[PDB]
Length: 350
Image (cartoon, rainbow, N blue to C red; front, side):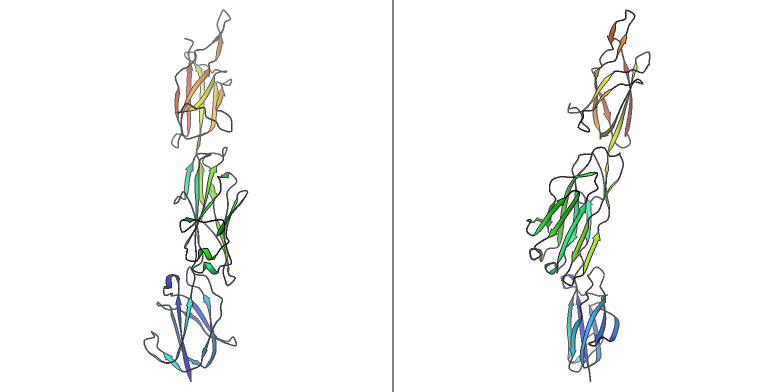
């Protein structure tokens, strides 16, 4: 006398789940069958089973779903048959419904959709970290998203967490922050049942003084433990911000003499007429012995150079005279395809 069983495997949104692999065991642990893969409709059908207690156990999870170690018991108590497509059933066929849950995933982007971003120092940009919220999140034990920002970066204010686009109280999700480490930990798992997207947004700035063109990478990580004590740890793909700055080289010479000049003072202003400040200091220069003023770490890109003090010289009557002051601004442009602007400035006695 022999019975049968029908395993009905489903996934997200009650979808029929194919490719889920199971083994069938007797209660005493002996393997009856292995490599039983759910068909296109999420079914595994087995007949010809001697009466008694059995249990299925998953050996391979469907792609994208969490592995499930649970031993699922059933009794074969009556006779039953079932053909391969289940269109014909006789007697009693034990029915087993097995649900699968997706495993959380992690995605990091810059300003929503970017994987790379050329940006000026001390200029705001966002890290957008989105993780999948599974259908059994309600039953999860741990769900944490972390991100340690490269130390060449400054966290701006307090990172914000959105669930399905809605900002959540510190009750449901707590945003912690210590040093460069940002950590958002789910605290109320019930307030997230039915939700699908965990979105952590960290606002950042690239510090001043990092070499231009240097790639500052970022990644975020998700840590979780589900109801079955399955522990996950995934890391996002790296995203990159690149500091954009340039160099301004001024060489101060004489009109006809063409000689290098020391002592000529200049200043760099933006097109709003305000002096440019870099490391807390205004961008000022005094011409060296070779008549050079080199300014580095200048963000993009439109500025105006002004002479604030002309060089001196001594005529034959020993006179202590200053060259003429240049009263017109010198427009400069800094931007890739023009990252180092070298300008020669001629200086007239009258």
